Structure formats: structure tokens, C-alpha cells
Length: 108
Length: 108
Image (cartoon, rainbow over all chains, first blue to last red; front, top):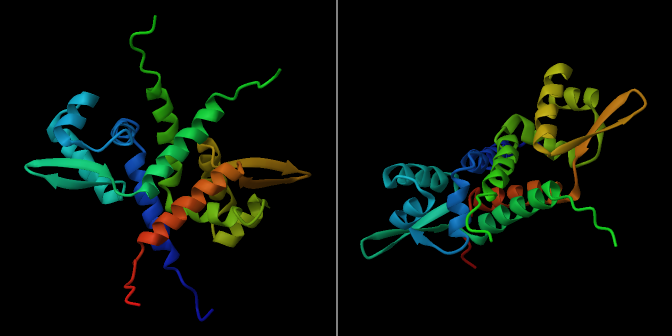
């Protein structure tokens, strides 16, 4: 209670940070693809129709946000969602948006 | 038959939209405040130390993302989290953020 703890602003900073990474749309194609399995940069880029150079750039953007991480198998860099925390969050935002855009008139 | 149709792309646009709303720290504080109950613009503005007109813009942005809804009674415009689903999202990301905000050292 002494004074006030504004450290929560750093918490909001992290929330905004992951938001900035997610807010793009095209980079969500990466998350969606990684949710189907962890993949190498070459695989992710080509599959989504993006250049490897540009992919590495925005993968680092997602990595710094805290969405994805990278593992080195041999000489390939495989990207995977940092943790199920972000994975389930991405699944959540997909579902919550889906059932709102597809607001079905359930009626029998 | 159905060969190829990229419909998921529009779904990602909606996700990017809510991401932009979450990418605003000043407005995230409002979400944490409105998670405590529905309150009129005047109350929200004063509590945060922001102008009513500016707060309205902040609130409108959140509402446009689908974060909060406008529940009007009498002569007051109360803002509240659009749904429990959305509240659980903000709660989730807040927990995820906090979980990464200094994980500390557990040596017991």
C-alpha cells in the first residue's frame, strides 16, 4: 500500500508487446502453421509464400514479442510456439472470433 | 468440388483487429479497470486521469475491436467487457505476461 506499484505498466507493456506481434494478420499465418507442428524457416516461408529473408525478420519480431522460439536441429532453425501459453491464447482468439463472425442461428 | 479457397485470411484480419486493441497500453489499463464492473465514461476518465473526450476515443477503439461493449442506462454510458470470453482472454494474457515478468528463482 506504501505509495503505489506502477510495475503493472510493465505487465501491460508485455501484453501490448505480444499484441504488436500478433497485430498484422499475415504473421498469423506463421502461428497457424506452427500450431500444426514446428517447422524450419525454409519450410514456413515457402509454405506461406513469403521470402526466407523477410520471414526471419518477422519471426524475430514474433520471437521478441514472446510468441515463438527457435530450436537448432543440425543446421536448420526450427520455429515453435514459445509455450502452450501463447498457443492456447492464439487458439482462444481464433475460436472467440470464429463463433462471433459465424454467429449461427441455432434453431431446431 | 472444393479445391482451394483462402477464407481463413479474413479470420486473421479479425484477429489482427483485436490485437491492435490490445497493443495500446493506455487502453489496457482501462480493460483492467472495466473488468471490475461497468462504469460510465465520466467515472472511467476521472479514475484514469484522462479527458472524457479522449477516454471516449480510447473506449471506442476498444469497442471497435470487440473488447468492450456500450451499455447505456439513463443519461450515462457505461462501458464493460463485451463478454466473459473476452475477459478470460485479457485475464489469460495478463497471467501470461505476469508469468514472464521476472520468473524469479525457485530453489526450494
